[PDB]
Every structure is written in structure tokens, then in C-alpha cells.
Image 1 (cartoon, one colour):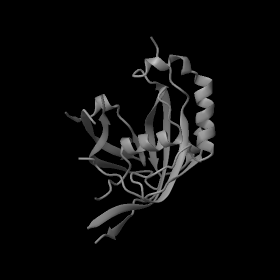
Image 2 (spheres, rainbow, N blue to C red; image 1 turned 90 degrees about the horizontal axis):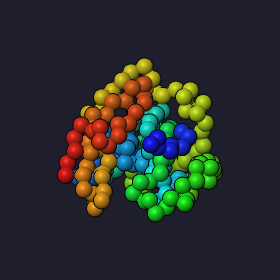
Image 3 (cartoon, rainbow, N blue to C red; image 1 turned 30 degrees about the vertical axis):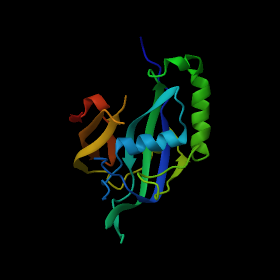
Length: 194
């Protein structure tokens, strides 16, 4: 049958520091799909649905900062990311069929975005507080990235885990085009480890 999916939602997430790592410390230069999945689920999470992050726009110049601990951690600095995402019903939770109420969950998602998320938002790690704000589709599409006009292949990046502790990790060639990273689905990734 055709599967339900929500409208697109759009959010601006910003922070002074970010640390996106490869679970398997220096940051990747841009967020992993996994870290973005984390941020959208901190905005609003129910076992009834699954948030699907489809696209991110890297708005700011990529800059890093070093922190020595006594022994180095390299962070991104002064980050702004616009995330496009939607949700679908969670087919791993068939028992929650009576809660599959699209108007209910779409309304709550909009309210949750507007008030900066129902939970604390972190940029890849707990010491890196993020700020979530509401943007519209229009703002998403028209905001100019620092990287507009060029593409960069960031090489192979951690994408996400698969669970029944993880059963699989997924990695894939990640290319930022005009600042835009359009995600592949897990099963379309270049590399799967069991």
C-alpha cells in the first residue's frame, strides 16, 4: 500500500561548538545523519513514528577549534544547519496503531519546533548545547549557504546504525553541493558492516 508520511518540517539548529564523531576525537566537518536523527528526536519523539532526516544545509564557513585535555579534541565552531525532515509510522511498533494520528503528531511537532524542542538539543556530544528554532519552507529554500557555488566530497562518513546494541553500521560517500547534503537511505549506503 502507499505509506503515510508527514509534511516536511524545517528547523534551524545553531551552536558555538559541535563534535560529530565516528562511533567505531576530531569532528567530521559536517553532521552525520545519526547526529541529525538525534537532534530531531530531541525535538519530538514517540515510538509511534520514526523521524526521517532527508536533507541538511550547512550555512556557515567550516571552522574548527582545538581543546587540549590533561589529549586533544577538535571541534567545529560557530555552526548553523537547516534540517529538512518528516516522519512515517514506525512499523516496528504495530501495537501503537491507535496512536497513528497524523493531525495530532503534526501539530505537536510544529509546537515542539517552535519552543525549541521538548528535550535538550546537543550537537554530536553532551558538552555542545544547540539551539533549535522554527523556520518555514520558504526560509529553508532561500537561505544562502556560505558554500553556495561549490561542491565538496567529504569522502566516506558514518551514516547510522541498524538495531534489532547495533547489528550493523552504515558508511557512505557524502558530498556537500552548494552547502546541501541530501541523504541516502541506510540501505543505499556504500558500505555496511555487520
